Image 1 (cartoon, one colour):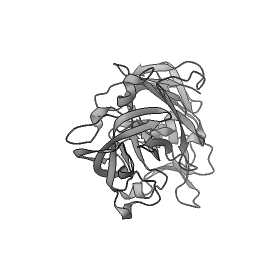
Image 2 (image 1 turned 90 degrees about the vertical axis):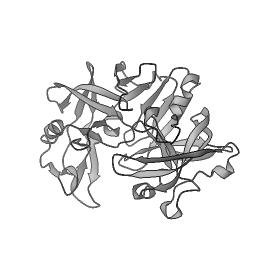
Image 3 (image 1 turned 180 degrees about the horizontal axis):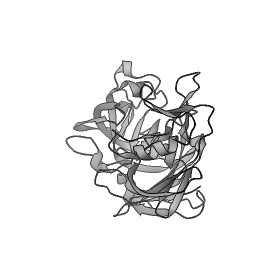
Image 4 (image 1 turned 120 degrees about the vertical axis):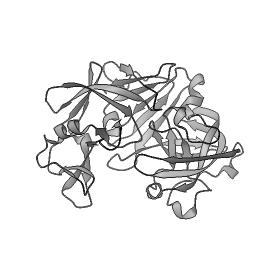
Length: 330
């Protein structure tokens, strides 16, 4: 089997991407944030505290003839940005782009943090990291991909995120028309439950490539590119007037600037992030100070190749017995 679904930016800055997902019978379509940095499929629901729902579409398990309470199961997750959610668990039928999994754990939110409430466009998350990170207790549950894997034509999914435009998540096949050149594959460590890999270095603009190992994660659920302070300083030093602002919470730059590109290595291959991808717009409405898309990972404890990086590439998440990651230009 295969599946193919369009993923769409939630706003003009590409702050996140949503993908429609069919849950239950008859189908209830919710727009979920596909997140290769976590492993829970959770949704706003009829059980979510009313004051914490503000415009989201909810899953109502009582209206699904295939929903079953997973007795005694609860979940609770905290993300790197300090947001969180928790609740109980149903199993139900879940389909993405024509690919159907029966008996998928659908984690129903009873509580969500304010950041989730405030994002009316995101109805929940669909985790695509390794199932060892799944938070359901006392019986850990499998991700949608893990459940689908054996049925797929090939045990892969691909992320093809657009810049200010829709893109695609495919399951079970590699669309050879979706990228240019060849796909370069690189080793993955699953030790921390992430799609963790090591970039071979970087360049700023038209500058020389610096060969240096940068361990980090491919994370579709994180907006920005978080890299070591040395790398980030070298990037922003090429932008007149750019500075790290403790009050704002990262590097800012004059909105009048033209940003240089940023290149990252994948083995001997190179992925070029155009400068415009690194512009996240005014820090507040009407400001001439703009927020940067490349930020320091110091104090995160891990480097994160988030959407800023991934949207410059066609990315293969290869879930073979020994997982790997592939990157192509597009």
